[PDB]
Amino acid sequence: SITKTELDGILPLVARGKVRDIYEVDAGTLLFVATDRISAYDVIMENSIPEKGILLTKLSEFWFKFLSNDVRNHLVDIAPGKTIFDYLPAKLSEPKYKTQLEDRSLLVHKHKLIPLEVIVRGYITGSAWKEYVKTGTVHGLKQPQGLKESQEFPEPIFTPSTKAEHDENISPAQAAELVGEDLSRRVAELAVKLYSKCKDYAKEKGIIIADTKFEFGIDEKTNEIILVDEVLTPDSSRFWNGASYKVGESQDSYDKQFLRDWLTANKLNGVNGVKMPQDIVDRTRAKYIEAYETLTGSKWSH
Ligand SMILES: N[C@@H](CC(=O)O)C(=O)O
Ligand SMILES: N[C@@H](CC(=O)O)C(=O)O
Ligand SMILES: N[C@@H](CC(=O)O)C(=O)O
């Protein structure tokens, strides 16, 4: 596994998030390195899931292509017969660095950020369900009465959040205050379009994507909106097994239930520095491979 990248200053670090290590390539370009780190109950595990970051990078490359005629993205075009390493300083091709970067890294253009977590919900679950049970609203938005847990909304809904800085669920009106009325409306409409297309596809493959979180940027030189993070993975979305879907109850987490159940059984939920046992690592890894193969139609290792 690649847990924490160590590039010895060859590129400056921009950020280390829960999963991605982000480096600055040059004035206009970033390198997004998806590590094998995994979180549960909003803490990072001590150890990693081998090749998780490769699988999730590739899954997202699949979705960018799937959506190529629907939305611009931040990827830098890599010329035919070249690799990312041709676009990086020579030292990063040395074995000690190439091993940390190969297959899990994306070269991306910097863009003007739109500072919103653009969540679209197709189904009522998570924090939305919690709110709804108490007050009959979702992100302050009035909902129909009688929704059951995990039920589909009449139409998928834009339900923005800030970024922590935990994240705060906000209304569309607040999003308009933050980023502008016109821009927020356009972001909302686009995100719902992208979500619906991908949710429908995934459902025919057997996975219900209950919700997903996008991040967008803008081209100030055209007003165009651009995806500025990778999309539609189990880290950015709530995946459920479609065959087992049943309203009125919670769904197993497609990706993380095995891990969550182990943590819960040991009173380790929310605890930092927790090493997952090998059987939990292996099974979680296998579940990422199954997600990847199911959604992309490609084979991981054959
Ligand atoms: N999605 C993770 C959230 C986290 O632990 O950061 C979970 O399934 O519990
Ligand atoms: N590759 C373009 C985006 C696009 O092709 O739509 C860019 O990096 O800005
Ligand atoms: N109509 C918006 C502009 C935007 O789309 O950001 C406003 O100035 O509030």
Image: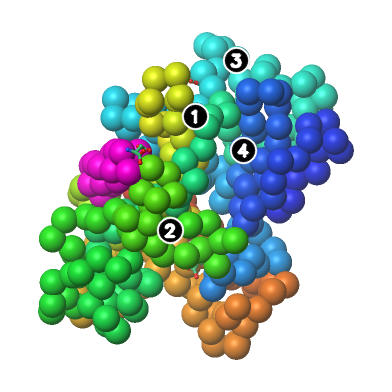
Instruction: Return the residue at label 3.
Output: 82
- Distance from label 2 to label 1 (Cα)? 22 Å
Q: CA distance from mark 2 to mark 3?
A: 38 Å
Residues at marks 1 and 3 touching, judged by CB atoms closer than 8 Å? no
Image height of 8 relative to 212, above or below: above
Q: CA distance from mark 1 to mark 3?
A: 18 Å
Name the front one of labels 2 and 3.
2
* Amino acid beneath label 3: Lys
Q: Please, what secondary structure does the residue beneath circle 3 have?
A: loop
Residue at 58% across / 64% down in the picture? 39
Q: Nearer the viewer, residue 223 or 232?
A: 223
Q: Which one is earlier in the sequence, the residue at label 4 or at label 3?
A: 4
* Residue 183 part of the magenta-drawn span: yes
Mark 2 touching mark 3, by CB under 8 A? no
Residue of label 4 = 32
Image spot of residue 297 (x, y percent): 34, 39
State the residue at coordinates (32%, 55%): 172
What crowding class fits label 3: few (fewer than 14 Cα within 10 Å), some (14-19), or many (20 or more)? few
- Mark 2 or 1, closer to the camera: 2
Is residue 262 shown in magenta? no
Image position of 105 with respect to 28: above or below: below
Q: What span is in magenta?
A: 181-199
Q: Position of residue 112 (x, y in %)?
A: 52, 32
Give the residue type that dot 4 points to: Phe
Mark 4 Cβ and ligand 2 under 8 Å apart: no
Asked if ligand 2 lies within 8 A of label 1, the reply is yes
